[PDB]
Every structure is written in C-alpha cells, then in structure tokens.
Length: 113
Image (tube, rainbow, N blue to C red; front, side, top):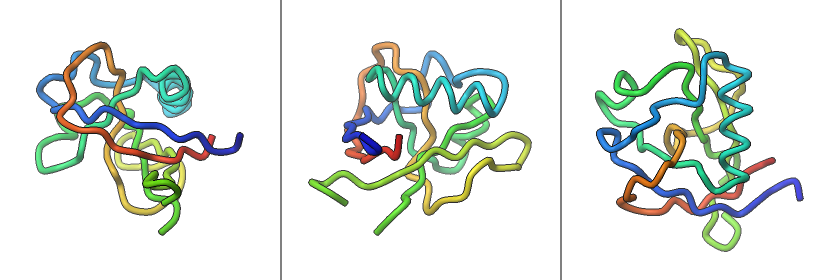
C-alpha cells in the first residue's frame, strides 16, 4: 500500500529517552520510516522550547492534504541546521523512537509510505 493507517503515541518531551533517529538527514528519515512500520515511533507536539530538547536532524510529520477514517494524511520532512529536506503542510509534531514511554494521547495519521 502507498499509505498506512497509524496511531502514533504522543509523548511529553521530558519523558523521551531516545531524542532522535540518528546523525544524517538520510539516516533519520530511514530510521523514522522503519520505526513507523514497526510501530516503535512516538510523536512530540512542537511548542516553545521543545525542539532544543531533541537531537538534530529532526523528522517532522506534516499534513499533506485537507482525513480518511479520522487519519490525517502526512509525510516526512527532515531538518538540519535550519534546512528542510521535503516540502509539505503544517507540522503535526516531531518523530522520536518509542521505547515504552507512557503517552498522553494518540495521533491517527495516514502515512504516505
């Protein structure tokens, strides 16, 4: 399938134990895609002071369309030193590895895979 319905656990930034996917734009996008497929991917909602608590490069999920079965359509955009790799809509949050942190909510997304 070109798209996969996912429910992403929403994590508080101060709970997150692994604060990024790796060390290059290509690696973080790769790792994010693998974790999204394996159901081992969390979402941190971006507010004032969140991103400097996480590791660059960042992986964002961004709205790709204006929501089948409640799932918002999204795609991945990476960022390193203020340059983004991809072009998409509004940020729903930043992706991080999920290693058993207790979520505060779930974000239903339809991922262009």
